[PDB]
Image 1 (spheres, rainbow, N blue to C red):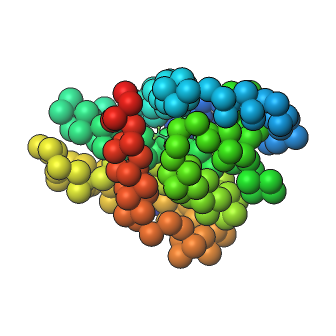
Image 2: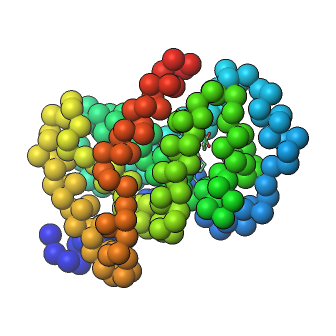
Length: 223
Ligand SMILES: CC(=O)N1CCN(C(=O)N2CC[C@](c3ccc(C(O)(C(F)(F)F)C(F)(F)F)cc3)(S(=O)(=O)c3ccc(F)cc3)C2)CC1
């Protein structure tokens, strides 16, 4: 493919993302002032770990649906065999949610948008996972500090889903070509937007997997 075809791929991936971004960026930034009261935090803190794991897993399932809808809106992904479409979505859907999460994160007060309002990491106190909640706040802080754009999330998550390294793939070569083109599309877009600077400042690829595997470990016990 040509440089015009790489540009078209960027546009397409960014179009698919915007159509499935779940919550509008403009809405999320406006709601940054809409913070939960002390009695509202207390209300969540009083809830059972099972009630909180039920709510979090409900929102996670909901978020994963938009991720599946994002991958379904990618031409190359649809061309893959069903087993490969499943293998990539099972291994990457939750990792994509953890990346998408930075839009709902506010670095000015260390709060995240959860159930209509912004709340601190003390909102999730009931789970008994202070280490795990800190880990997802720190990860969203590492991306929000960089001011990770909508298009940047779009291309990064496309690379998270399309990874030929995943075990269980039959058409590894086909996925490799899709990964290579998206890698080329990501770097080309960073040049066009003068964001080459953020590449070295991004999470060390393997960290997202370390964070996700530790979370599925805690989740599998309750779901
Ligand atoms: C704007 C946008 O696209 N968004 C923002 C709103 N959404 C979220 O942020 N979502 C949807 C579900 C969210 C979510 C649920 C559960 C986890 C866990 O790691 C857990 F251990 F923490 F529980 C897992 F259960 F996996 F173990 C992680 C994320 S959430 O909103 O419930 C949430 C946000 C911040 C947070 F500290 C904790 C939870 C993330 C969806 C994506």
